[PDB]
Image (cartoon, rainbow over all chains, first blue to last red; front, side, top):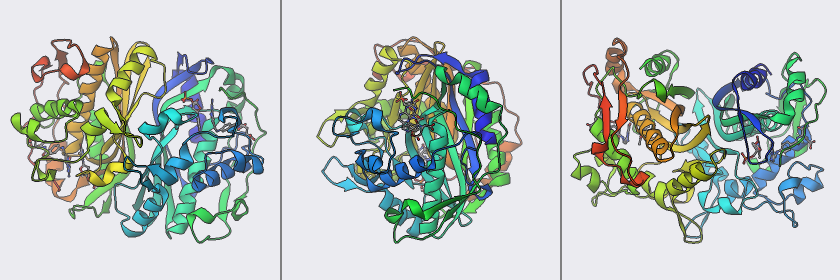
Length: 264
Length: 264
Ligand SMILES: Nc1nc(=O)c2c([nH]1)NCC(CNc1ccc(C(=O)N[C@@H](CCC(=O)O)C(=O)O)cc1)=N2
Ligand SMILES: Nc1nc(=O)c2c([nH]1)NCC(CNc1ccc(C(=O)N[C@@H](CCC(=O)O)C(=O)O)cc1)=N2
Ligand SMILES: Cc1cn([C@H]2C[C@H](O)[C@@H](COP(=O)(O)O)O2)c(=O)[nH]c1=O
Ligand SMILES: Cc1cn([C@H]2C[C@H](O)[C@@H](COP(=O)(O)O)O2)c(=O)[nH]c1=O
């Protein structure tokens, strides 16, 4: 996509070589924002083939409040394998904070049900937020939340969402993260009877890993194709009842996939 | 400042009329980002006089972990009066989350000391974050955290910081919020022996209140003056030992102040 290839080029032209946690090394910039009008098409990268199966099942797993990778394995999705322990656990990452944030006094808060109630009863609220950055449980998480905090906004009957992503692997992570949150906005808009507005992505440390440079130059030579259209075939009873089969991505015709190593 | 007056104009040209919590009504946009290179000057608005006394003491109060307004009153700062209860309490807002985030198992986490330790021992970390959005205590807070989440970044010996502000009163709140966080970056950089880099401000619902329109048009006719220079006269033993007298803002010569009503 235009916005995405502009960011890849910006990291190549402006990024600082930086060491990182994995020992791979990165070219890095800090602070970037891009906006996707979801009315223009579903923002799935076309200059390389993205594995939709992994994107959709990872979002359905988050909405279940699940942090064990068994569900992903049942559905042949292996993207979280390298961080899980012997029992397949990841600790209280995304799904657990979204669905069951533990309070100091022992209660659990379901942020997704809270957001539904706010969108249905107080759409003008400036407080419609979900946060996975639970400071008191960071030490139990396999990987600290990268897409950490997001906010919904309603104006003129359209639902928008902004994500703050503290750390962004531009070649591998970001195509998945954009499609995942664009999908959640479509689901939320359908459940609340709203039209989809904008998805606003904001990044903190936005980086290309040093061993993704050949793949980056290859993808940068490709022309973006027309964005596909997302079709949700059914309106489930709730946001927690969607099924993989309910989604149709129409007209997706990408350039070939480009493999790249994951930095662990 | 150039960036600030460009945002005011953008809200006037592109904002949607929106109802809000206070009943005042706003012109609102969602998702904006601006960057201030702190090497260019201290980003204190010059097209209206800002009350530095309130800005500096509010930051020192946050760093103490204090949420009762008595300290502010001792220093003749009245900006939080309308939200405090009979005992002057605001509930577990900013200072308390920054200095003593309560964990599910009863521990308290001092995020500021954690950040100091990360900047001193692992400056390349992509996880150097402070969050005031504590989901399990939102219901005890007088006002939900508006400047909610921020991240530090170190590259080429320079310290940068990005703030996610979920809700932004452009005329009253934002001049104070920009100066406050720019001041914290200078303090952190001095304590860690770094140069100051960029302050990146990212907003969610960014708005002008309907009864600030005359004040906005007046300020938009003024030309920005040169930015002042911040001088910290002393290096305290720690980030918690700064005093009001340690700060000097040199060459601040603003246009006259513009009064405007606060929406409660
Ligand atoms: N270094 C790093 N970058 C990541 O983006 C990342 C990470 N670490 N930690 C875990 C994680 C979880 N999400 C993801 C997303 C995509 C792939 C991935 O390897 N995608 C490949 C193959 C997809 C497949 O399994 O079919 C791709 O080519 O997109 C891995 C993990 N993301
Ligand atoms: N509607 C709203 N907007 C705010 O920016 C705001 C709020 N509510 N809730 C509390 C709060 C706390 N921060 C602030 C910042 C500035 C002023 C204020 O009134 N500033 C005036 C006078 C400063 C003074 O007391 O000397 C100004 O003209 O800047 C109030 C509260 N900020
Ligand atoms: C989980 C996840 C990680 N990442 C990234 C960002 C970093 O490259 C790495 C996480 O490492 P970090 O915790 O040191 O920042 O994986 C994404 O880009 N998207 C994701 O969804
Ligand atoms: C505390 C604080 C509030 N605000 C704002 C944003 C909103 O106008 C209002 C808070 O209301 P809200 O919680 O309904 O968003 O005050 C700032 O802009 N800066 C601040 O530091």
